[PDB]
Amino acid sequence: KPVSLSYRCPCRFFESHVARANVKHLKILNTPNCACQIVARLKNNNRQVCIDPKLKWIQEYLEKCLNK
Amino acid sequence: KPVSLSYRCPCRFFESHVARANVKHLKILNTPNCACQIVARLKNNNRQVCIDPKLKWIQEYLEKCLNK
Amino acid sequence: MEGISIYTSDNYTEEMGSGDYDSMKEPAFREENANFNK
Amino acid sequence: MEGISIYTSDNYTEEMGSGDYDSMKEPAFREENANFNK
């Protein structure tokens, strides 16, 4: 995969109807071109997909880890 | 490595005086024994360290990713 | 969102990954889509 | 808050891990460190 920093995002499009329980963990990356993207490693060996950091289950996830 | 329910935790303790600029990304996992742990991969090749999910830069990191 | 000095993407390179699962955007924190296939 | 059902340990098991870099606890969102050296 040829890459550069001029136009770099881990995903241009992030996934929203993806299951919370179907992930093994969250991997979050902040690229210069795109705000914030979370990438989850899906169960078994399917692949790893980008989850919207603004998704519902992510919202509660971040918040709870932060303090509450 | 056997991790059932008795003892599964991705970290021992969470690191606080660790640099935001020295990490490549955040990897978050929740084990049954431990609340929330973010583990970050240090730049180049050192290892991966556990970051307090409640660290300053993490707080705002979660916040920015959340929406704000 | 802001052009703030972030970290460097060392191991994780990327530039434009794709999306599935009805790849959508904007906080979906409060939405009531209660399984409606009609 | 409470421990909800978690993700199956496939890629990541771990019952051990790191804990250095002056390992501390609680939100450090607000720190007012005014020269700690005496």
Image (tube, coloured by chain):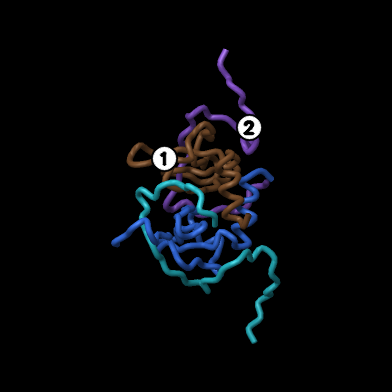
Chain colours: A blue, B brown, C cyan, D purple
Residue occupying the point 43% across, 60% down: A9
The amino acid sitting under disc 1 is: Gln
Q: Is residue D31 left or right of residue C19?
A: right
Q: Is residue A27 above or below residue D22?
A: below
Looking at the rendered structure, the secondary structure element under dot 1 is strand
Q: Which mark is residue A7?
A: none
Foreground label between 2 and 1? 2
Q: Is residue B40 above or below residue B66?
A: above
Q: Which mark is residue B48?
A: 1
Q: Quadrant of residue D36?
A: top right
Mark 2 belongs to chain: D
The crowding category of the residue bearing disc 2, from other C-alpha atoms within 10 Å (few below 14, some 14 to 19, many at least 20), is: few
Residue occupying the point 40% across, 47% down: C8
Along the line of sight, which residue is nearer the eye, A11 or B21? B21
In the picture of the structure, the residue carrying the numbered disc 2 is D31
Q: Residue D10: image x %, image y %?
A: 43, 53
Q: Residue furthest bottom?
A: C38
The amino acid sitting under disc 2 is: Glu
Is residue A13 in view?
yes
